[PDB]
Amino acid sequence: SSHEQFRAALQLVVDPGDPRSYLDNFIKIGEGSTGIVCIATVRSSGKLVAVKKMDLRKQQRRELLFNEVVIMRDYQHENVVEMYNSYLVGDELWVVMEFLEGGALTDIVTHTRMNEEQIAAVCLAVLQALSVLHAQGVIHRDIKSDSILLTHDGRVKLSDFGFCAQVSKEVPRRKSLVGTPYWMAPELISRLPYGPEVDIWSLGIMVIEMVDGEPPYFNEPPLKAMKMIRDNLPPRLKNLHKVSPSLKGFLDRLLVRDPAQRATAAELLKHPFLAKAGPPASIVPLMRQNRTR
Ligand SMILES: Cc1cc(Nc2nc(C(=O)N3CCN[C@H](C)C3)nc3ccc(Cl)cc23)n[nH]1
């Protein structure tokens, strides 16, 4: 059947063999929409790595499994989690990656208020990554706080590229409904032709996460949230009167319904709000203590 075809094709783009020849003591530490995240130990090194496992049979869009392993192969950027190897183990794709020991931004957002120096530092890191990716024609398509990982010393890296897409001169736009509902851009929900700008909208929703503690419409059923994103004015900060005019002006350039008028990552790197961006040391306290909103 087509599963055997897809499996054979995937085997052609991953590394050969079974990584159980060198990885020990798998422990599940998390999960997302396509599979689970484990930690494992290198038998020779004592080195810790992260291993994502994705069952080919459980994917709504299995062809998307190719994209990450291929597009992000050998990708080296200071704000992108490094991928080391990938394997086909039975009916599962395993991707071996660098282990980020500060956890995900989501755990920060649910447990502590962030100040604007810290929000700006996160935005700056993500935009440095997106500026390079977008210039290369890569759309991430799952920007949200759970896709953002931290080191213990406060460095910020983008992960979870499993929904990513490649655009080009010949095919400059995608139309697939891909992402996580509450973060999806309205043109993407509408299945209109879209480009890298969808990531900028999603980043705007993540700024609302950092300020408010959750995205708009978060306890709404996801299909209803998507209709409200598609049809209503851009969502507002609950804590609108608590943020600076600079932060609001920045957000106003991200949450723009018309994708042609939404700011690009390269434009946003010039925005004065990002002059507030603190160094990694400013992020460290957020992983060690809690402060209520
Ligand atoms: C690829 C990778 C992940 C990672 N560290 C982590 N990933 C996940 C986890 O399971 N996630 C977070 C990202 N989004 C996934 C869908 C689910 N949870 C963690 C909890 C505590 C600490 Cl200390 C590190 C974590 N290092 N390298």
Image (spheres, rainbow, N blue to C red):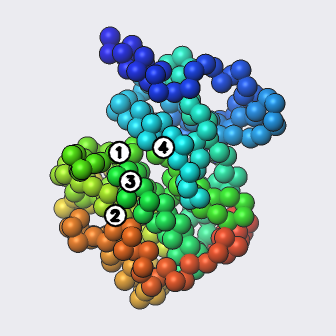
For the point 21% across and 67% down, the residue is: 260
Local secondary structure at mark 1: strand
Please tell me which of labels 2 and 3 falls first in the chain: 3
* Location of residue 67 in the rendering, given as x and y in whole percent from the top left corner: 40, 38
Residue type (three-letter) at the residue carrying disc 1 = Ala
The answer as to whether callout 2 falls within 8 Å of ligand 1 is: no
Residue ID for mark 3: 136
Mark 2 vs mark 3: give the one in front. Answer: 3
Q: Nearer the viewer, mark 3 or mark 1?
A: 3
Give the label on residue 72, or none.
4
Residue, far top: 1
Q: Gap between marks 2 and 3, in whole Å?
A: 19 Å
Residue marked by disc 1: 165
Viewer-side residue, 35 vs 275: 275
Q: Nearer the viewer, residue 87 or 170?
A: 170
As helix, strand or loop, the secondary structure at mark 3 comes to: loop
Displayed quadrant of residue 85:
top right
Label 4: which secondary element: loop
Q: How many marks?
A: 4
Within 8 Å of ligand 1, the CB of disc 3? Answer: no
Q: Which residue is mark 2?
A: 201
- Crowding around mark 2 (Cα neighbors within 10 Å: few <14, some 14 to 19, many 20+) is many
Do the CB atoms of the residues marked 3 and 4 lie less than 8 Å apart?
A: no
Name the residue: 70% across, 69% down. 284
Of marks 3 and 4, the one in the foreground: 3
**79 with respect to 184 (left or right):** right
Q: CB of mark 2 within 8 Å of CB of mark 1?
A: no
